Image: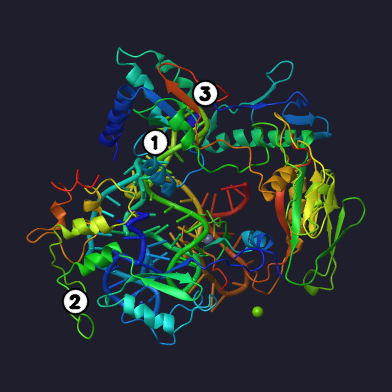
Amino acid sequence: MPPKFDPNEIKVVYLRCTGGEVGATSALAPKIGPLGLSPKKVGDDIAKATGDWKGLRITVKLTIQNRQAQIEVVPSASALIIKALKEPPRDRKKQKNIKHSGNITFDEIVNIARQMRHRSLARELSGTIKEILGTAQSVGCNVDGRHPHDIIDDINSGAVECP
Amino acid sequence: DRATWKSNYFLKIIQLLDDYPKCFIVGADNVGSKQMQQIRMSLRGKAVVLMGKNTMMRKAIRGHLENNPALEKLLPHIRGNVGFVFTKEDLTEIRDMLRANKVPAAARAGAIAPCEVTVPAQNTGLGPEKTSFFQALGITTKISRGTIEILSDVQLIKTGDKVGASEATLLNMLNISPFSFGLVIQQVFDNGSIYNPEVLDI
Amino acid sequence: IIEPSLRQLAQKYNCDKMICRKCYARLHPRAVNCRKKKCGHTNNLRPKKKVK
Amino acid sequence: MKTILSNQTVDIPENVDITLKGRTVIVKGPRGTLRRDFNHINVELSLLGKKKKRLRVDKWWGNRKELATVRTICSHVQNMIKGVTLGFRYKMRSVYAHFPINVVIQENGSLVEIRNFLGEKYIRRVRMRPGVACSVSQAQKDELILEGNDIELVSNSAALIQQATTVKNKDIRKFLDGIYVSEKGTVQQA
RNA sequence: GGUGGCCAUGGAAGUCGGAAUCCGCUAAGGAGUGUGUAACAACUCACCUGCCGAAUCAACUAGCCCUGAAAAUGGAUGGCG
Ligand SMILES: [Mg+2]
Ligand SMILES: [Zn+2]
């Protein structure tokens, strides 16, 4: 990419959000996608197969360019997994009682959530992120018969196993 | 906020002045909030960066403890943005050297510092003619095919002399990035000692 | 057409103004009070409208 | 409430020699000599510093609104000192969409002659005050330089041409043309 | 920053609107005062720093004057003042 219009591989990053099935309403990326040798349709519908077999409730979506190859990975977002940690999937055409539904445990699955929080956080080790991603709730409301409310004060686990 | 929360900070500074006898005085004139987040995690094995305000002139009140003396030599340096970085594992320079990361560089008109600045007779690569920042001063240049050269060399500005605005802007156009030393290190304290970054100190 | 730094000079002198809601008198950006005796020195100020 | 005393010392430099005739301050440095009368304000101007180091303005049985003025005299005196040492320079850069404002100084300073502002046939003329040397700049395109010793005189004169150049019956949000002050500074900076 | 947070998608990733709604880095930064931006950004403001040196600020309430306050043969604190 540099004095004159060069490249030298294609290993260039682009990130997208949102996802029903895929797209397709005379639309996908454009702007970044078209000049880049990608398309709007085949590299759209191959974004189905990988962002599929269950994602249908908004996604984050890194697409890596290689010549004209668009790699369709679903990189997990902290609230997206906590929406998919739900008593899950009702999907579309009802839904209707809406997405403020809100009752889901994640007792050690938030441990697995704060585990898969890959790098991002620049972390004090669990016992603080456990509280960061525990505190970001609105749907669920903490562990079987509790509220996030009173986990924040304490967490008698994780701490010295994650370092 | 702030007769209790104040009186709280006081108990955490007085702690690290006792427990931590190795003190690194750091100048963070240019800094980002995402920058420090990364510097503390890049030095998590080692150091403890401590950021306060005016109140840092409360080394007096730990020195008041009918106790410590040589903390008088810490008095002239609590001024003009400063924080300290308390560390157990130090061990001299060798962790201090690996801290120095990318940065100024910078270079501004009205500055003074480090050593004799040179621009090795190398071919620049800027757009053609672009000779006006050389022609304004005086260096022998030539268009060999397309791009520009200096076909000679010398020191542009010497130690103690002021750098003009046109001679500053030409140096940062060339990519030559000297005159700087902010967010790095100002003055060490290790056991009543007075180090000085002019150079043994490391 | 009219270079940015040049423009935002003239803007400084004709556009960023407070204005009295009583007397329509035109005032500097900081004004919390009018100049004029006629309105009764009001405090009812608004910013002058930025051209779309 | 009357305040028994208020005062202020101006620190006079080694270059200049102020000498006050009662209340009337005269100032002579390198550049020239200035004068001004504070035969209104009513204060006590002493020159206490020997060799010659301090103007001190008193004020004395003064209520709030005259206490103000202690500092204002104190200012027009600094402002003189800066004028007779350094001298001031207001720069003013002409501004437009379209018709080139076409300036031409015409005795020495004095007549600043302006064709074509907004296609107007009437050639605006503007006098400077005495001691104000206008001149068309170089090292920049549409830009005047008003030099003088006296702030008062130099900035009416900026403002005279800044105000002579005003549009009528338009949007002055849109019609941002005319000549206006870009930089108040000095001749010599030090 | 965790962070296209949630609702809303028409865009609202801090921001036409609302439930809300809290941690990290902490120093300190509101899941935001605004500009504005389709949305951002970019800017700004809370918060917090750098530089300076001692008084500073806000809401009320009153005293005095200023405004509200506009009429027809010329013009009346009695006049002069
Ligand atoms: Mg019209
Ligand atoms: Zn008014």
Could you say which is closer to the camera, residue E49 or residue D114?
Answer: E49
Indicate how the structure is coloured in the image.
Answer: rainbow
Answer whether residue A68 is visible to the viewer in this image: yes
Could you say which is closer to the camera, residue B77 or residue A117?
Answer: A117
Q: CA distance from mark 1 to mark 3?
A: 24 Å
Q: Residue at x 38, y 83 (%)?
A: A45
* Badge 3: residue crowd in 10 Å (few <14, some 14–19, many ≥20): few
Between label 1 and label 3, give the one nearer the viewer: 3
Query: Which x, y percent locates residue E13?
Result: 37, 65
The kind of secondary structure element at disc 1 is: loop
Q: Amino acid at mark 2?
A: Pro
Q: Chain of mark 1?
A: B
Answer whether residue B26 is visible to the viewer in this image: no
Q: Is residue D156 left or right of residue D122?
A: left
Q: Chain of mark 2?
A: A
Q: Which mark is residue A89?
A: 2
